[PDB]
Image (cartoon, coloured by chain):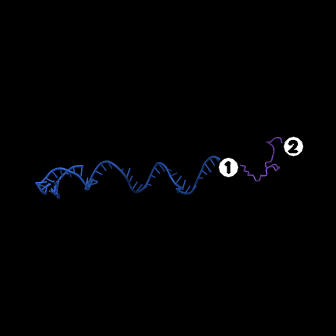
Chain colours: A purple, B blue
Amino acid sequence: AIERLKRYRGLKNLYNCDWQVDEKDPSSPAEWKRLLRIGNYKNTKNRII
RNA sequence: CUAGUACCGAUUGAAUGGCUUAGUGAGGCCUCAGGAUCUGCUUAGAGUCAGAGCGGA
């Protein structure tokens, strides 16, 4: 069970967990800082136009 | 950060409308004049040959 499943964290509730977004785990894509990240898409869109 | 809501207040920017000072004023109508032209009569041009003179539009 360990070698099959060690990657699984286990949680009480997804809505309450503190899972980090840009997690450093190795299966995360090579591009992260390479990716564009925006936040307020609404306030970006209308501003650009 | 964004949204919403308002005040003044600068340009008169740049316009719309009412009132008002001063000055100007189209057009037709009435009236004082003017007379391009057209035409009747008359002594008189000829057996249309001119001129003048008295009228009308």
How would you rate the neighbour count of disc 1 (Cα within 10 Å): few for under 14, some for 14-19, many for 20 or more? few
Q: Which type of secondary structure does the marked residue at label 2 adopt?
A: helix
x then y, percent, for residue B29: 32, 48
- B2 to the left or right of A22: left
Name which residue lies at 66% across and 49% down: A46
x then y, percent, for residue A22: 79, 49
The three-letter code of the residue at mark 1 reads Lys
Kindly indicate the quadrant of the structure image that contains residue B13.
Answer: bottom right
The three-letter code of the residue at mark 2 reads Arg
**Marker count (numbered):** 2
Name which residue lies at 87% across and 43% down: A4
Q: Quadrant of the N terminus of chain A?
A: top right
The chain under label 1 reads: A
Name which residue lies at 69% across and 50% down: A44
x then y, percent, for residue A41: 70, 48
Name which residue lies at 88% across and 44% down: A3
User: Extreme right residue here?
Assistant: A2
User: Marks 1 and 2: in contact by CB < 8 Å?
Assistant: no
- B51 to the left or right of B31: left
Pick the front one: A31 or B40: A31
- Residue bearing the label numbered 2: A4
- Residue bearing the label numbered 1: A45
Task: Nearest to the eye among marks 2 and 1: give it.
Answer: 2
Q: Which type of secondary structure does the marked residue at label 1 adopt?
A: helix
x then y, percent, for residue B42: 13, 53
- B24 to the left or right of A29: left
Pick the front one: A20 or B7: A20
How would you rate the neighbour count of disc 2 (Cα within 10 Å): few for under 14, some for 14-19, many for 20 or more? few
Q: CA distance from mark 2 to mark 1?
A: 44 Å
